[PDB]
Image: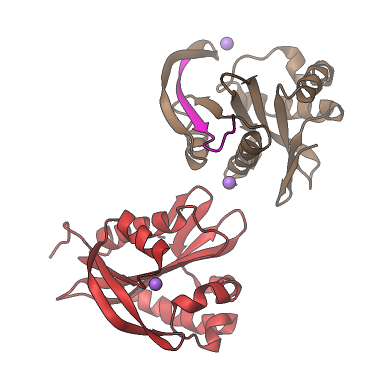
Chain colours: A red, B brown
Amino acid sequence: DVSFEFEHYQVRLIKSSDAVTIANYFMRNRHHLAPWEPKRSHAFFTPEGWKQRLLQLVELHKHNLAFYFVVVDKNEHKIIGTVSYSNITRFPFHAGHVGYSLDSEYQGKGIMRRAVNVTIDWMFKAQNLHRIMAAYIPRNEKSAKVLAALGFVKEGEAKKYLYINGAWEDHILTSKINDDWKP
Amino acid sequence: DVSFEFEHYQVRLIKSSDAVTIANYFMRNRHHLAPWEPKRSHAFFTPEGWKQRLLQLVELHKHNLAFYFVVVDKNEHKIIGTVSYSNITRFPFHAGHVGYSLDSEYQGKGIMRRAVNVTIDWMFKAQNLHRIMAAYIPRNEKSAKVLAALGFVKEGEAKKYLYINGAWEDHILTSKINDDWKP
Ligand code: NA
Ligand code: NA
Ligand code: NA
């Protein structure tokens, strides 16, 4: 099954047996991630909430409708990042949205750059997507740099795009196009 | 002295008291190592040979001239690996050579990568080395992957470099440079 390794990390599809570790990761990083993401339900921080979500994701993956990757620190046996491909459409768009997160203690190590690059490559080659879209709040410099480094091209800006922490936030829209897409 | 622990392992400087256990380790891995390393004398595989060797090493440790680390399985109280920093030069090179080995029953667990990573980090930060050199036979894929994972950069190739098991063996030359070295 789908697995990528570099240094002491492993990037792979999330599994049902990840329920506790993924809940631990979002609990651990609750404060760090809170100002950048929409309001989260209680189930989002719990292993029982993730048990249910994982049932849905297994089903989504069966139909090639979603691909939720975790970044594992093999030294620590814990999840330290996520790379999620969602809102996948086939004909006539062949597009998906990518969203990612990283543990607050693993910043500035090029992990997100690598994890996203290897998964985009797989989404293009193994899943035959034509387009991956990403959107980030302009003051999220780390996110901007990652996307630029990976050859995502800025497409414009949607003002007041997503409701986060009680306010509409502008987002830069960016995308990467797969020239080798097969009809 | 210097000590690193992870899982059920400890990486530390070798000591006089290790004479028997280091001997057992090389005697245990004699055959797995013969195709990969230079011919060793008989004394290399005896506790008495190491007593002497250790008296020299203990001395090199004292004047920061050499750092011979062992990897210990704390559960079994056995040495299962080595990481040796030798050929150390201060001004105007600030460089040394790393050589390492792992017990053949302990392969595939990333033990070597972690042992070398944590000690390179110490050589850079606590010993202020500028450069660590490593060289490997191209068909030693296990060694190549360790070095790649730790960010060693290929500098070239030395044909017919070391005489091993009755023939001169080509070696890839690699290094890691400490950008934070202080003059
Ligand atoms: Na953002
Ligand atoms: Na490591
Ligand atoms: Na020989």
In the figure, B135 relative to B159: above or below? below
Q: Is residue B116 left or right of residue A179?
A: right
Between A128 and A7, the one nearer to me in the picture: A7
Between A21 and A29, the one nearer to me in the picture: A29
Question: Which region shows up in magenta?
Answer: B169-183
- Quick check: is B37 in the magenta stretch? no
In the figure, B56 relative to A14: above or below? above
Q: Is residue A31 left or right of residue A56?
A: right
Residue B27 position, x and y percent, is: 73, 25
Can residue B87 be seen at all in this image of the molecule? yes
Between B64 and B113, the one nearer to me in the picture: B64
Between A79 and A32, the one nearer to me in the picture: A32
* Magenta span: chief secondary structure: strand
Q: Quadrant of the N terminus of chain A?
A: bottom left
Where residue A158 sits, quadrant-wise, is bottom left
Residue at 57% from the left image edge and 44% from the top image edge: B108
- Quick check: is B179 in the magenta stretch? yes
Can residue A129 be seen at all in this image of the molecule? no
